[PDB]
Image: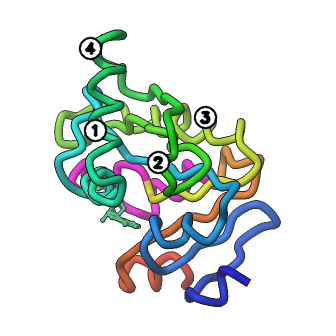
Amino acid sequence: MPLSNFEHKVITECVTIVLGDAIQVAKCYGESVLVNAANTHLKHGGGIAGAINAASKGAVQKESDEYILAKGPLQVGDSVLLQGHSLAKNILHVVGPDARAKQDVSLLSKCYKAMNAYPLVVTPLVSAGIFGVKPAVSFDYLIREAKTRVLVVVNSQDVYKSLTI
Ligand SMILES: Nc1ncnc2c1ncn2[C@@H]1O[C@H](COP(=O)(O)O)[C@@H](O)[C@H]1O
């Protein structure tokens, strides 16, 4: 039982909240799709994006640079399915809105709808770090959209406590 390794709370038959590292959660599930909380240029310099890139030994960034050079930058709310690099079956790069730039927070709906294409998704709370969206607000957008099995992973115990009462 992969989740026995982690404190967690089942919210619905779709959505479970997990305390830990989303990369280590996804490693337990060979058929999971791991969500990267990315920016429009897929520049994975810090945050969960930097951690995912480091776990891939830089391979994620090389793949992202090829994609962006070929396709041009993404829009806020866009998502792109790329290779998993042995971290997960695939990695879904999702561009959440940046509240610092007063971008439309409701674009999180579009971000989370994109996860419904996959039978099992491991995701952080998109935009919930430096992009300035409060975790409970990002969770609100997630639970409204999720139609598949989603493990929502938070690496702060204070965030986990606040989300589980
Ligand atoms: N490995 C991780 N696993 C789960 N959550 C993370 C991880 N790294 C960062 N976070 C949090 O997930 C949210 C989105 O990450 P970020 O896009 O980097 O702001 C923020 O609340 C981060 O603090």
Residue of label 4: 69
| Magenta residue check for 146 | no
Q: Is residue 159 left or right of residue 16?
A: left
| Label 1 vs 4, first from the N-terminus | 1
Residue type at the position of mark 3: Ala
Residue of label 1: 61
Quarter of the image for residue 90 reads: top right
Instruction: Tell me the residue at 71%/42% (across/down).
Output: 118
Instruction: Tell me the residue at 62%/64% (across/down).
Output: 151
Q: Nearer the viewer, residue 28 or 7?
A: 28
Instruction: Tell me the residue at 76%/60% (across/down).
Output: 14
Indicate which label's residue lies in the foreground, 4 or 3: 4
Task: Provide residue 142's location: percent of width, then percent of height.
Answer: 58, 51
Residue of label 3: 114
Residue type at the position of mark 4: Leu
- The segment highlighted magenta reads 126-142
Cα–Cα gap, marks 1 and 3: 21 Å
Residue type at the position of mark 2: His
Q: Nearer the viewer, residue 136 or 71?
A: 71
